[PDB]
Amino acid sequence: GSWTEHKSPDGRTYYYNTETKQSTWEKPDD
View 1 (cartoon, rainbow, N blue to C red):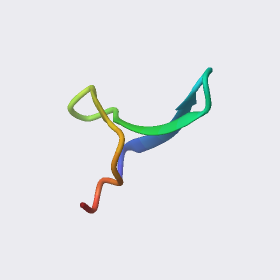
View 2 (view 1 turned 135 degrees about the horizontal axis):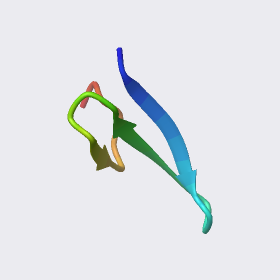
View 3 (view 1 turned 180 degrees about the vertical axis):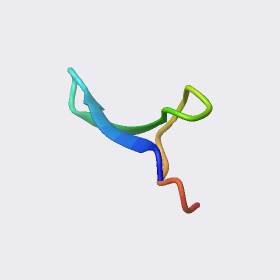
View 4 (view 1 turned 180 degrees about the horizontal axis):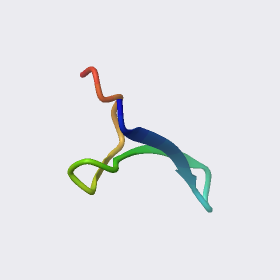
């Protein structure tokens, strides 16, 4: 449980893991 939900300034909700310092467009439970 270390995934932060942040949306781009263009209107794109993306998830970013603080543990792996990675980012994705799909939920962490894909």
